[PDB]
Image (tube, rainbow, N blue to C red):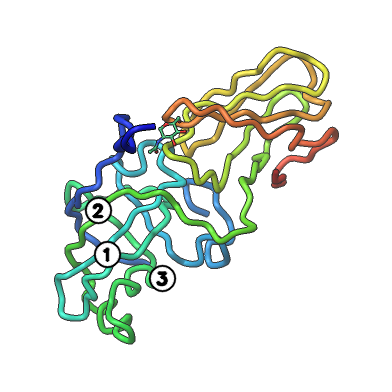
Amino acid sequence: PKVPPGPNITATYGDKWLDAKSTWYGGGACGYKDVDKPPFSGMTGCGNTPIFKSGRGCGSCFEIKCTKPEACSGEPVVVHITDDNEEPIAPYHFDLSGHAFGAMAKKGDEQKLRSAGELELQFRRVKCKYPEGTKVTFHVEKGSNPNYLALLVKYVNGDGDVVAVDIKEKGKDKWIELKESWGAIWRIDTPDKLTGPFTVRYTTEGGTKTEAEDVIPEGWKADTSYES
Ligand SMILES: *[C@@H]1O[C@H](CO)[C@@H](O)[C@H](O)[C@H]1NC(C)=O
């Protein structure tokens, strides 16, 4: 096979560090619920427009390091973007949670640092790392009836943002294309009842179409999460 081929020449997120202002806080736009519990575990933060990207960036994970105040470890920590930072104060502005903010400090200085209020950090997008056992969850948003479906596609550790979500009822052969809306909520209204079990197929930025067969059961209920 000759000599090992170097990395595939494909479009990708950088690998260089970007600069952003950072502050913290102690029902987000992305619709995530128990953020203190796994897989996020408090490692979350509000991200402004170029990070949130109207919702497309809800699963987003970023490495964030800090060298500014003395308490900063200079070591990187991964944060999951769970909301929208409507009031940015710099080109890039991360509004991290208290836990996340402090997580950039030297062992035991998490509070000393959290007292800094604002600081300058460096960040770069990275593939999320969820604890094993974590499965891509599809949440049927409330307001869904048998003629309207609106769902979230959580924990897709994929490469990029999911850019399309389709469903197929166990029995038919045509794909129903969902429309993207703010908060990464895919929606579809139809004349035909949305009864039978649906297979959800979501494709990521790359082009990688992955399917979750019959994940949404017949007789599903609004505001309920079903996993694969
Ligand atoms: C390059 O792309 C192919 C097809 O997706 C994949 O199987 C292969 O492992 C990739 N190579 C590297 C070095 O990542």
Say how many tags the image has.
3
Q: Residue 112's quadrant in the figure?
A: bottom left
Q: Quadrant of the N terminus?
A: top left
| Disc 3 + disc 1, Cβ < 8 Å | no
Residue 83 percent coordinates (x, y)? 42, 50
User: Residue drawn at (33%, 50%), measured in percent from left and top?
Assistant: 47
Residue on which disc 1 sits? 23
Q: Is residue 69 above or below residue 147?
A: below
User: Residue drawn at (50%, 27%), measured in percent from left and top?
Assistant: 180
Label placed on residue 208: none
**Badge 3 element:** loop
**Badge 2 element:** strand
Task: Residue type at mark 1: give it.
Answer: Thr
Residue ranking furthest to the bottom: 108
Q: Nearer the viewer, mark 2 or mark 3?
A: 2
Nearest to the observer: residue 104 or residue 126: 126
Nearer the N terminus, badge 2 or badge 1?
A: 1
- What's the CA distance linking mark 2 and mark 3? 17 Å
- What's the CA distance linking mark 2 and mark 1? 8 Å
Q: Is residue 125 above or below residue 5?
A: below
From the viewer's perspective, tell me whether residue 181 is left or right of residue 88.
Answer: right
Task: Residue type at mark 3: give it.
Answer: Gly
| Disc 2 + disc 1, Cβ < 8 Å | yes
Residue on which disc 2 sits? 93
